[PDB]
Image: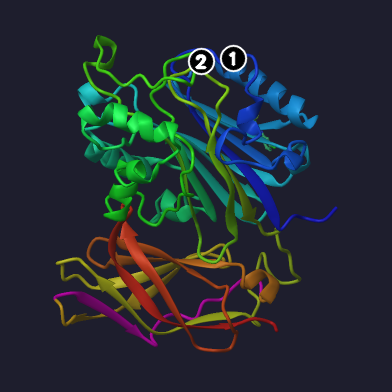
Amino acid sequence: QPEPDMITIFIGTWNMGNAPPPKKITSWFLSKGQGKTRDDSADYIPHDIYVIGTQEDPLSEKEWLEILKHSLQEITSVTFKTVAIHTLWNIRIVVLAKPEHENRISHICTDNVKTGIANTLGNKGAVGVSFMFNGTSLGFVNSHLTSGSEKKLRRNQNYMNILRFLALGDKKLSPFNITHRFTHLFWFGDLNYRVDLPTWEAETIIQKIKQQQYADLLSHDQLLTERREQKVFLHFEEEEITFAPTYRFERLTRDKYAYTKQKATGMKYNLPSWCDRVLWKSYPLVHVVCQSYGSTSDIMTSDHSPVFATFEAGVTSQFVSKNGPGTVDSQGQIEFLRCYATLKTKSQTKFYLEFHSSCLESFVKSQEGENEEGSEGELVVKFGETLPKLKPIISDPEYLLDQHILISIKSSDSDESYGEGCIALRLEATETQLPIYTPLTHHGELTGHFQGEIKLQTSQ
Ligand SMILES: O=C(Nc1cccc(Cl)c1)C(F)(F)F
Protein backbone atom coordinates (compact mmCIF):
# COMPACT_ATOMS: atom_id res chain seq x y z
CA GLN A 1 0.00 0.00 0.00
CA PRO A 2 2.11 2.96 -1.27
CA GLU A 3 2.43 6.28 0.59
CA PRO A 4 0.93 9.21 -1.29
CA ASP A 5 3.01 12.05 -2.80
CA MET A 6 -0.15 14.18 -3.26
CA ILE A 7 -3.40 14.66 -1.30
CA THR A 8 -6.45 16.79 -1.84
CA ILE A 9 -7.67 19.10 0.89
CA PHE A 10 -11.14 20.68 1.18
CA ILE A 11 -11.36 24.00 3.02
CA GLY A 12 -14.80 25.36 3.95
CA THR A 13 -15.70 28.63 5.63
CA TRP A 14 -19.23 29.52 6.63
CA ASN A 15 -20.59 32.24 8.90
CA MET A 16 -23.85 30.50 9.90
CA GLY A 17 -25.49 33.68 11.28
CA ASN A 18 -26.41 31.89 14.56
CA ALA A 19 -29.02 29.76 12.66
CA PRO A 20 -29.12 25.98 12.26
CA PRO A 21 -28.16 24.73 8.82
CA PRO A 22 -30.71 23.42 6.32
CA LYS A 23 -31.15 19.65 6.00
CA LYS A 24 -28.85 19.30 2.97
CA ILE A 25 -25.45 21.03 2.73
CA THR A 26 -23.77 18.58 0.30
CA SER A 27 -23.26 21.28 -2.42
CA TRP A 28 -20.68 22.87 -0.08
CA PHE A 29 -18.49 19.73 0.12
CA LEU A 30 -18.96 19.12 -3.63
CA SER A 31 -17.65 22.63 -4.55
CA LYS A 32 -20.88 23.39 -6.51
CA GLY A 33 -22.40 26.84 -7.02
CA GLN A 34 -20.66 29.98 -8.26
CA GLY A 35 -16.97 30.62 -9.00
CA LYS A 36 -14.34 27.99 -9.80
CA THR A 37 -16.37 24.79 -9.26
CA ARG A 38 -15.51 21.12 -9.18
CA ASP A 39 -16.25 18.77 -12.14
CA ASP A 40 -19.38 16.58 -11.69
CA SER A 41 -17.25 13.54 -12.62
CA ALA A 42 -15.38 13.96 -9.28
CA ASP A 43 -18.47 13.98 -7.01
CA TYR A 44 -17.91 10.49 -5.57
CA ILE A 45 -14.11 10.97 -5.10
CA PRO A 46 -13.47 11.85 -1.45
CA HIS A 47 -10.96 14.51 -0.53
CA ASP A 48 -8.24 13.17 1.74
CA ILE A 49 -8.81 15.87 4.41
CA TYR A 50 -11.82 18.16 5.00
CA VAL A 51 -11.30 21.27 7.13
CA ILE A 52 -14.52 23.07 8.08
CA GLY A 53 -14.41 26.58 9.64
CA THR A 54 -17.60 28.09 10.98
CA GLN A 55 -18.37 31.47 12.55
CA GLU A 56 -21.51 32.44 14.43
CA ASP A 57 -22.01 28.64 14.80
CA PRO A 58 -25.02 27.94 17.11
CA LEU A 59 -24.58 24.14 17.19
CA SER A 60 -22.83 22.01 19.78
CA GLU A 61 -19.66 20.20 18.62
CA LYS A 62 -21.66 16.96 18.67
CA GLU A 63 -24.53 18.39 16.61
CA TRP A 64 -22.19 19.73 13.90
CA LEU A 65 -19.99 16.57 13.81
CA GLU A 66 -23.14 14.47 13.16
CA ILE A 67 -24.20 16.77 10.28
CA LEU A 68 -20.71 16.87 8.77
CA LYS A 69 -19.96 13.16 8.97
CA HIS A 70 -23.42 12.10 7.67
CA SER A 71 -23.05 14.67 4.80
CA LEU A 72 -19.68 13.24 3.73
CA GLN A 73 -20.89 9.64 4.08
CA GLU A 74 -23.89 10.44 1.81
CA ILE A 75 -21.55 11.96 -0.86
CA THR A 76 -18.69 9.46 -0.72
CA SER A 77 -19.95 6.32 1.11
CA VAL A 78 -16.88 6.80 3.40
CA THR A 79 -17.11 7.20 7.17
CA PHE A 80 -14.56 9.93 7.96
CA LYS A 81 -12.45 9.96 11.13
CA THR A 82 -12.45 13.05 13.30
CA VAL A 83 -8.85 14.41 13.54
CA ALA A 84 -9.65 17.47 15.65
CA ILE A 85 -12.39 19.88 16.66
CA HIS A 86 -11.83 23.16 18.51
CA THR A 87 -14.26 25.94 19.38
CA LEU A 88 -13.75 29.49 20.73
CA TRP A 89 -17.14 31.08 21.49
CA ASN A 90 -19.02 30.52 18.19
CA ILE A 91 -15.85 30.12 16.03
CA ARG A 92 -15.13 26.45 15.24
CA ILE A 93 -12.78 24.30 13.22
CA VAL A 94 -13.33 20.59 12.39
CA VAL A 95 -10.75 18.37 10.65
CA LEU A 96 -11.96 15.10 9.13
CA ALA A 97 -9.79 12.56 7.30
CA LYS A 98 -10.31 9.37 5.29
CA PRO A 99 -9.87 6.30 7.54
CA GLU A 100 -6.84 5.09 5.48
CA HIS A 101 -5.00 8.22 6.81
CA GLU A 102 -5.47 7.45 10.50
CA ASN A 103 -1.87 6.08 10.94
CA ARG A 104 -0.38 8.84 8.71
CA ILE A 105 -1.64 11.67 10.98
CA SER A 106 0.11 12.55 14.24
CA HIS A 107 1.25 15.53 16.38
CA ILE A 108 -2.26 17.02 16.40
CA CYS A 109 -2.33 20.52 17.98
CA THR A 110 -5.24 22.93 18.59
CA ASP A 111 -5.26 26.49 19.85
CA ASN A 112 -7.25 29.71 19.81
CA VAL A 113 -6.55 33.43 20.01
CA LYS A 114 -9.02 36.02 21.36
CA THR A 115 -8.57 39.41 19.57
CA GLY A 116 -9.17 42.94 20.98
CA ILE A 117 -9.17 44.48 24.52
CA ALA A 118 -12.13 45.15 26.95
CA ASN A 119 -14.96 46.44 24.57
CA THR A 120 -13.38 44.55 21.61
CA LEU A 121 -12.56 41.25 23.50
CA GLY A 122 -15.48 38.81 23.63
CA ASN A 123 -16.44 37.37 20.29
CA LYS A 124 -13.72 37.77 17.55
CA GLY A 125 -10.57 35.67 17.19
CA ALA A 126 -9.34 32.48 15.67
CA VAL A 127 -9.11 28.73 16.14
CA GLY A 128 -6.54 26.46 14.54
CA VAL A 129 -5.35 22.92 14.07
CA SER A 130 -2.00 21.50 13.00
CA PHE A 131 -0.72 17.99 12.46
CA MET A 132 1.85 15.97 10.56
CA PHE A 133 0.66 13.97 7.52
CA ASN A 134 3.60 11.56 7.09
CA GLY A 135 6.62 13.88 6.43
CA THR A 136 4.51 17.01 5.76
CA SER A 137 3.32 19.57 8.37
CA LEU A 138 -0.15 21.04 7.80
CA GLY A 139 -1.65 24.07 9.58
CA PHE A 140 -5.19 25.45 9.41
CA VAL A 141 -6.55 28.73 10.83
CA ASN A 142 -10.22 29.77 10.95
CA SER A 143 -10.53 33.42 11.98
CA HIS A 144 -13.55 35.69 12.52
CA LEU A 145 -12.06 39.19 12.27
CA THR A 146 -13.52 42.53 13.36
CA SER A 147 -16.60 43.61 11.37
CA GLY A 148 -17.47 46.92 9.75
CA SER A 149 -16.38 48.69 6.56
CA GLU A 150 -14.32 51.37 8.45
CA LYS A 151 -12.30 48.80 10.51
CA LYS A 152 -9.85 47.41 7.97
CA LEU A 153 -6.88 48.44 10.19
CA ARG A 154 -8.42 46.57 13.18
CA ARG A 155 -8.74 43.49 10.94
CA ASN A 156 -5.06 43.84 10.02
CA GLN A 157 -4.19 44.09 13.73
CA ASN A 158 -6.36 41.01 14.46
CA TYR A 159 -4.37 39.11 11.77
CA MET A 160 -1.01 40.01 13.40
CA ASN A 161 -2.25 39.05 16.89
CA ILE A 162 -3.47 35.65 15.56
CA LEU A 163 -0.21 34.80 13.72
CA ARG A 164 1.87 35.93 16.75
CA PHE A 165 -0.04 34.12 19.46
CA LEU A 166 -1.62 31.02 17.88
CA ALA A 167 0.54 28.17 19.23
CA LEU A 168 0.46 25.41 16.63
CA GLY A 169 3.09 23.07 15.19
CA ASP A 170 6.54 22.21 16.50
CA LYS A 171 7.27 24.23 19.69
CA LYS A 172 11.02 23.60 19.06
CA LEU A 173 10.68 26.10 16.16
CA SER A 174 10.83 28.85 18.82
CA PRO A 175 11.78 31.84 16.57
CA PHE A 176 9.03 31.04 14.07
CA ASN A 177 5.37 31.99 14.06
CA ILE A 178 2.70 29.96 12.28
CA THR A 179 3.55 31.63 8.92
CA HIS A 180 6.81 29.58 8.91
CA ARG A 181 5.97 26.38 10.83
CA PHE A 182 4.10 24.43 8.13
CA THR A 183 4.77 22.94 4.72
CA HIS A 184 1.25 24.15 3.89
CA LEU A 185 -0.73 26.74 5.91
CA PHE A 186 -4.39 27.46 5.08
CA TRP A 187 -5.95 30.58 6.61
CA PHE A 188 -9.67 31.09 6.08
CA GLY A 189 -12.73 32.49 7.77
CA ASP A 190 -15.02 35.48 7.96
CA LEU A 191 -12.14 37.88 7.45
CA ASN A 192 -14.77 40.66 7.18
CA TYR A 193 -12.98 42.86 4.60
CA ARG A 194 -15.46 44.89 2.57
CA VAL A 195 -15.94 46.42 -0.85
CA ASP A 196 -14.98 50.03 -0.16
CA LEU A 197 -17.37 52.06 -2.32
CA PRO A 198 -19.71 54.88 -1.28
CA THR A 199 -22.94 53.87 0.46
CA TRP A 200 -24.90 55.76 -2.27
CA GLU A 201 -23.52 53.15 -4.78
CA ALA A 202 -25.33 50.16 -3.11
CA GLU A 203 -27.84 49.64 -5.95
CA THR A 204 -25.08 50.09 -8.57
CA ILE A 205 -23.05 47.36 -6.81
CA ILE A 206 -26.12 45.04 -6.79
CA GLN A 207 -26.57 45.72 -10.54
CA LYS A 208 -22.93 44.77 -11.20
CA ILE A 209 -23.36 41.53 -9.20
CA LYS A 210 -26.52 40.58 -11.18
CA GLN A 211 -24.47 41.01 -14.39
CA GLN A 212 -21.63 38.87 -12.93
CA GLN A 213 -19.29 41.84 -13.50
CA TYR A 214 -17.00 41.75 -10.45
CA ALA A 215 -13.88 43.61 -11.73
CA ASP A 216 -14.87 47.14 -10.54
CA LEU A 217 -15.95 45.63 -7.21
CA LEU A 218 -12.78 43.52 -6.63
CA SER A 219 -10.61 46.62 -7.36
CA HIS A 220 -12.18 48.07 -4.12
CA ASP A 221 -12.03 44.86 -2.03
CA GLN A 222 -10.18 45.81 1.15
CA LEU A 223 -8.37 42.48 1.50
CA LEU A 224 -6.95 42.69 -2.08
CA THR A 225 -5.96 46.38 -1.61
CA GLU A 226 -4.46 45.87 1.85
CA ARG A 227 -2.54 42.82 0.55
CA ARG A 228 -1.24 44.78 -2.46
CA GLU A 229 0.01 47.51 -0.06
CA GLN A 230 1.69 44.81 2.13
CA LYS A 231 -0.50 45.70 5.16
CA VAL A 232 -1.75 42.13 5.79
CA PHE A 233 -1.31 38.52 4.67
CA LEU A 234 2.21 39.15 3.31
CA HIS A 235 3.43 36.13 1.26
CA PHE A 236 -0.01 34.43 1.20
CA GLU A 237 -1.85 33.41 -2.00
CA GLU A 238 -5.55 33.61 -2.88
CA GLU A 239 -7.23 32.17 -5.98
CA GLU A 240 -8.99 34.68 -8.25
CA ILE A 241 -12.54 35.43 -7.03
CA THR A 242 -15.15 34.62 -9.72
CA PHE A 243 -18.23 34.20 -7.42
CA ALA A 244 -20.62 36.89 -6.16
CA PRO A 245 -20.09 38.61 -2.82
CA THR A 246 -21.05 36.17 -0.05
CA TYR A 247 -22.47 38.79 2.37
CA ARG A 248 -24.97 40.25 3.28
CA PHE A 249 -28.01 38.27 2.02
CA GLU A 250 -31.60 38.23 3.15
CA ARG A 251 -32.10 34.78 4.73
CA LEU A 252 -34.07 32.00 2.92
CA THR A 253 -33.33 33.33 -0.60
CA ARG A 254 -30.16 34.42 -2.44
CA ASP A 255 -32.10 36.90 -4.58
CA LYS A 256 -31.57 39.89 -2.25
CA TYR A 257 -28.62 41.66 -0.69
CA ALA A 258 -29.66 43.31 2.62
CA TYR A 259 -27.27 46.27 2.88
CA THR A 260 -29.23 49.15 4.46
CA LYS A 261 -28.47 50.35 8.01
CA GLN A 262 -30.73 48.89 10.77
CA LYS A 263 -30.74 48.97 14.59
CA ALA A 264 -29.63 45.27 14.39
CA THR A 265 -26.50 46.37 12.42
CA GLY A 266 -25.56 49.22 14.80
CA MET A 267 -26.85 51.58 12.10
CA LYS A 268 -24.03 50.40 9.76
CA TYR A 269 -24.37 49.70 6.03
CA ASN A 270 -23.26 46.27 4.84
CA LEU A 271 -22.57 46.82 1.17
CA PRO A 272 -22.14 43.46 -0.65
CA SER A 273 -18.70 42.12 0.21
CA TRP A 274 -16.38 39.13 -0.05
CA CYS A 275 -16.20 38.61 3.73
CA ASP A 276 -15.56 34.87 3.49
CA ARG A 277 -12.14 33.87 2.16
CA VAL A 278 -9.50 31.15 1.84
CA LEU A 279 -5.81 31.96 1.56
CA TRP A 280 -2.73 29.78 1.81
CA LYS A 281 1.05 29.86 2.16
CA SER A 282 3.26 26.89 1.31
CA TYR A 283 7.02 26.54 1.57
CA PRO A 284 8.91 27.43 -1.61
CA LEU A 285 8.78 24.89 -4.50
CA VAL A 286 6.21 22.61 -2.84
CA HIS A 287 3.32 21.60 -5.11
CA VAL A 288 0.05 23.38 -4.18
CA VAL A 289 -2.70 23.97 -6.74
CA CYS A 290 -6.14 25.44 -6.06
CA GLN A 291 -8.70 23.25 -7.88
CA SER A 292 -11.88 25.09 -6.70
CA TYR A 293 -12.78 28.41 -5.08
CA GLY A 294 -16.40 29.41 -4.95
CA SER A 295 -19.63 29.80 -3.00
CA THR A 296 -22.78 27.73 -2.73
CA SER A 297 -26.07 29.04 -4.12
CA ASP A 298 -28.55 26.66 -2.38
CA ILE A 299 -27.68 27.06 1.38
CA MET A 300 -29.67 30.08 2.56
CA THR A 301 -30.15 29.82 6.38
CA SER A 302 -27.46 32.46 7.00
CA ASP A 303 -26.85 36.01 5.79
CA HIS A 304 -23.55 34.60 4.43
CA SER A 305 -23.14 31.93 1.78
CA PRO A 306 -20.67 29.13 2.45
CA VAL A 307 -17.33 29.30 0.61
CA PHE A 308 -15.33 26.28 -0.54
CA ALA A 309 -11.77 25.89 -1.77
CA THR A 310 -9.95 22.69 -2.71
CA PHE A 311 -6.29 22.04 -3.19
CA GLU A 312 -3.81 19.50 -4.49
CA ALA A 313 -0.97 19.52 -1.99
CA GLY A 314 2.38 17.78 -2.27
CA VAL A 315 3.25 15.47 0.66
CA THR A 316 6.34 13.44 1.51
CA SER A 317 6.79 10.02 3.17
CA GLN A 318 8.21 9.38 6.70
CA PHE A 319 11.77 8.47 5.46
CA VAL A 320 14.03 5.86 7.17
CA SER A 321 17.62 5.03 6.17
CA LYS A 322 20.32 2.76 7.59
CA ASN A 323 21.76 6.01 9.15
CA GLY A 324 19.18 8.71 10.11
CA PRO A 325 16.89 9.15 11.81
CA GLY A 326 18.98 8.68 14.98
CA THR A 327 22.31 9.75 13.50
CA VAL A 328 23.77 11.89 10.73
CA ASP A 329 24.57 10.63 7.21
CA SER A 330 28.13 11.80 6.37
CA GLN A 331 27.36 11.54 2.57
CA GLY A 332 25.09 14.62 3.07
CA GLN A 333 26.03 18.28 3.69
CA ILE A 334 24.57 21.78 3.26
CA GLU A 335 27.03 24.67 2.82
CA PHE A 336 26.16 28.40 2.64
CA LEU A 337 28.59 30.63 0.64
CA ARG A 338 28.83 34.46 0.47
CA CYS A 339 25.62 34.93 2.56
CA TYR A 340 24.36 38.24 3.90
CA ALA A 341 21.26 39.54 5.59
CA THR A 342 19.93 43.02 4.73
CA LEU A 343 17.88 44.31 7.68
CA LYS A 344 15.54 47.33 7.99
CA THR A 345 16.42 47.74 11.73
CA LYS A 346 17.99 50.98 13.00
CA SER A 347 19.68 49.00 15.89
CA GLN A 348 23.47 48.16 16.13
CA THR A 349 23.74 44.79 18.02
CA LYS A 350 25.72 41.93 16.50
CA PHE A 351 23.57 39.22 14.84
CA TYR A 352 23.86 35.45 14.47
CA LEU A 353 21.74 32.97 12.50
CA GLU A 354 19.82 29.89 13.55
CA PHE A 355 19.12 27.13 10.98
CA HIS A 356 16.11 24.95 11.82
CA SER A 357 15.00 21.92 9.81
CA SER A 358 13.59 18.41 10.45
CA CYS A 359 16.51 17.26 8.20
CA LEU A 360 18.87 18.20 11.15
CA GLU A 361 19.10 16.44 14.52
CA SER A 362 18.68 19.90 16.13
CA PHE A 363 18.94 23.56 15.20
CA VAL A 364 22.34 25.12 14.41
CA LYS A 365 23.59 28.50 15.69
CA SER A 366 26.14 30.41 13.56
CA GLN A 367 28.93 32.71 14.65
CA GLU A 368 28.10 36.44 14.65
CA GLY A 369 28.11 38.15 11.27
CA GLU A 370 30.02 41.34 10.39
CA ASN A 371 27.86 44.49 10.25
CA GLU A 372 28.40 46.97 7.37
CA GLU A 373 26.36 50.03 6.19
CA GLY A 374 24.31 49.63 2.94
CA SER A 375 24.54 52.47 0.31
CA GLU A 376 20.84 53.45 0.97
CA GLY A 377 20.99 53.51 4.87
CA GLU A 378 20.50 49.69 5.49
CA LEU A 379 22.20 47.30 7.91
CA VAL A 380 24.01 44.51 5.96
CA VAL A 381 25.14 41.57 8.09
CA LYS A 382 27.88 39.59 6.27
CA PHE A 383 28.48 35.90 7.11
CA GLY A 384 31.04 35.28 4.30
CA GLU A 385 32.12 31.59 4.15
CA THR A 386 31.88 31.50 8.00
CA LEU A 387 28.48 29.62 8.28
CA PRO A 388 28.54 26.12 9.93
CA LYS A 389 28.34 23.13 7.51
CA LEU A 390 24.85 21.55 8.15
CA LYS A 391 24.82 17.77 8.72
CA PRO A 392 21.53 16.23 7.52
CA ILE A 393 20.21 12.97 9.04
CA ILE A 394 19.67 11.39 5.60
CA SER A 395 21.78 11.91 2.43
CA ASP A 396 19.40 10.28 -0.11
CA PRO A 397 18.51 13.03 -2.64
CA GLU A 398 14.89 11.68 -2.84
CA TYR A 399 14.59 12.88 0.76
CA LEU A 400 16.97 15.81 0.99
CA LEU A 401 15.87 17.77 -2.12
CA ASP A 402 12.29 17.83 -0.65
CA GLN A 403 13.44 19.57 2.58
CA HIS A 404 13.54 23.20 3.70
CA ILE A 405 15.79 25.26 5.99
CA LEU A 406 14.16 27.88 8.23
CA ILE A 407 16.52 30.80 9.03
CA SER A 408 16.20 33.22 11.93
CA ILE A 409 18.56 36.19 12.34
CA LYS A 410 18.86 36.92 16.09
CA SER A 411 20.33 39.76 18.12
CA SER A 412 23.37 38.68 20.19
CA ASP A 413 22.28 41.29 22.85
CA SER A 414 18.66 40.02 23.30
CA ASP A 415 18.49 36.59 21.50
CA GLU A 416 15.33 37.94 19.89
CA SER A 417 14.63 37.17 16.21
CA TYR A 418 14.70 40.21 13.91
CA GLY A 419 13.64 38.16 10.85
CA GLU A 420 12.56 34.70 9.75
CA GLY A 421 12.60 33.07 6.33
CA CYS A 422 12.75 29.76 4.52
CA ILE A 423 15.07 28.26 1.84
CA ALA A 424 14.02 25.26 -0.30
CA LEU A 425 16.59 22.47 -0.97
CA ARG A 426 14.73 21.66 -4.26
CA LEU A 427 17.80 22.81 -6.21
CA GLU A 428 18.55 22.74 -9.95
CA ALA A 429 21.85 20.90 -9.18
CA THR A 430 23.83 19.28 -6.36
CA GLU A 431 27.58 19.83 -5.68
CA THR A 432 27.03 23.23 -7.48
CA GLN A 433 27.03 26.76 -5.92
CA LEU A 434 23.53 28.15 -6.59
CA PRO A 435 21.90 31.42 -5.57
CA ILE A 436 19.44 31.32 -2.62
CA TYR A 437 17.05 34.00 -1.38
CA THR A 438 14.32 34.52 1.18
CA PRO A 439 12.55 37.63 2.39
CA LEU A 440 12.76 37.97 6.19
CA THR A 441 9.70 38.81 8.28
CA HIS A 442 9.02 39.33 11.99
CA HIS A 443 5.44 39.24 13.29
CA GLY A 444 4.60 38.62 9.60
CA GLU A 445 5.91 42.08 8.50
CA LEU A 446 8.90 42.54 6.17
CA THR A 447 12.10 43.20 8.12
CA GLY A 448 14.76 42.38 5.52
CA HIS A 449 16.23 39.78 3.20
CA PHE A 450 18.69 36.90 3.26
CA GLN A 451 20.64 35.91 0.17
CA GLY A 452 23.77 34.07 -0.81
CA GLU A 453 24.70 30.75 -2.34
CA ILE A 454 24.13 27.14 -1.31
CA LYS A 455 26.11 23.95 -2.18
CA LEU A 456 24.16 20.73 -1.43
CA GLN A 457 25.87 17.30 -1.31
CA THR A 458 23.58 14.24 -1.45
CA SER A 459 24.56 10.54 -1.75
CA GLN A 460 24.05 10.80 -5.57
O1 LIG B 1 -7.52 12.19 18.38
C1 LIG B 1 -8.52 12.25 17.74
N1 LIG B 1 -8.58 11.85 16.34
C2 LIG B 1 -7.48 11.33 15.54
C3 LIG B 1 -6.18 11.05 16.00
C4 LIG B 1 -5.23 10.54 15.12
C5 LIG B 1 -5.56 10.29 13.79
C6 LIG B 1 -6.85 10.55 13.34
CL1 LIG B 1 -7.35 10.26 11.65
C7 LIG B 1 -7.79 11.06 14.21
C8 LIG B 1 -9.81 12.75 18.39
F1 LIG B 1 -9.68 14.03 18.85
F2 LIG B 1 -10.85 12.72 17.51
F3 LIG B 1 -10.12 11.93 19.43
In the structure shown, which secondary structural element does the residue marked by tag 1 occupy? loop
Q: Which span is picked out in magenta? A: 377-394
- Residue occupied by mark 1: 22
Above or below, 118 relative to 407: above
User: As shown in the figure, which amino acid type bears the numbered disc 2?
Assistant: Thr
The reply, left or right, for residue 127 in relation to residue 299 is left
Rendering quarter of residue 375: bottom left
The reply, left or right, for residue 103 in relation to residue 59 is right
- Residue occupied by mark 2: 301
In the structure shown, which secondary structural element does the residue marked by tag 2 occupy? loop
- Residue ID at (82%, 56%): 2
Rendering quarter of residue 72: top right
x, y (%) of residue 58?
48, 14
The reply, left or right, for residue 331 in relation to residue 54 is right
x, y (%) of residue 234?
35, 54
User: As shown in the figure, which amino acid type bears the numbered disc 1?
Assistant: Pro
- Residue ID at (44%, 56%): 180
